[PDB]
Image (tube, rainbow, N blue to C red; front, side):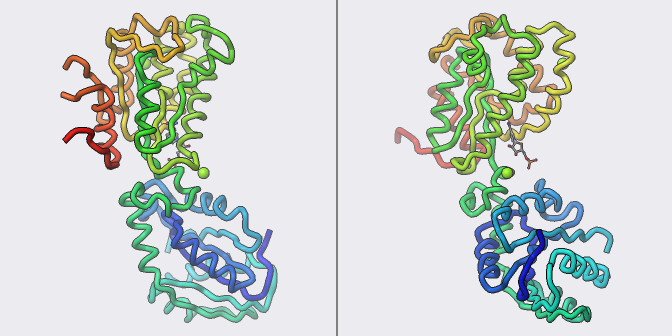
Length: 361
Ligand SMILES: NC(=O)c1ccc[n+]([C@@H]2O[C@H](COP(=O)(O)O)[C@@H](O)[C@H]2O)c1
Ligand SMILES: [Mg+2]
Ligand SMILES: [Mg+2]
């Protein structure tokens, strides 16, 4: 799993994120050399680490993004503890370890004049021919900066592996037979967005059990099962920058506190914590209890009638996890906004920046 050929090229980047600018250059470099070593640099709290893409995560995403290439290897250049001399020691250590042959024609592709200048001073006498080539990376670096500043605006250019991280997430929460499913569908269809289904609905249909028949192990199953489903939408190739999620672990954790014995709830507690902590939410739409009884079709037999009891615990728990600043309650139909959906789609506009057409003048 090392790089073959004589003419090999070295390409640098912080890749925060990798985008079609880098890629278009990287593939050009691959057509001119027998092989290419991508070198990701980073240090704690760097520009990428401050948006949640530390060097390690960026390196793994790169390996995944180029898992397909016979002649492209991804390598890590750890710039912690730096003083150019030791930096170059590591860089040529990378080259030596990740190459197969001797008598190489190595071409560095560098974008800053300081780097090329300090690199030319330090070619070691190891049988290789070294050249440093300058590249105008202004447009690539500006693009990566624009992407971090507003990912939704430059979404199509973000490499798909990195899109996993930059997605806005809207989660709809509320007791059943309150309209969530109609709401999630219409919100997501408004902006050509993907959406998830309430997993408890699908679990209860596939396993043919009612709300009162759920035991602890069923809740356990619904936690990881709803998360997988939401994670599947977050990472969908249909995602354009915003996804909508029909409930999450908090919802399930509200039902579980309300209906499980204390001991059985105490036992799901670690899985609840781990799952809820892994949930990135940007906007939380809460549908409050109302005397409506929507019933899109399927009836949660028991998760009705005590809607206020559910809504109080739900708000209790949303506070417990410090999420209230992301929360918007759709308290309409007797409050203002025209409909529950008008309020919601406008909140989607406030929190994600997407344009929404008005119906009237
Ligand atoms: N289920 C959810 O609400 C939710 C929200 C955000 C991310 N995720 C998942 O967790 C991961 C987040 O990765 P980062 O650590 O890069 O943010 C993603 O791969 C995604 O699939 C899940
Ligand atoms: Mg991924
Ligand atoms: Mg508690």
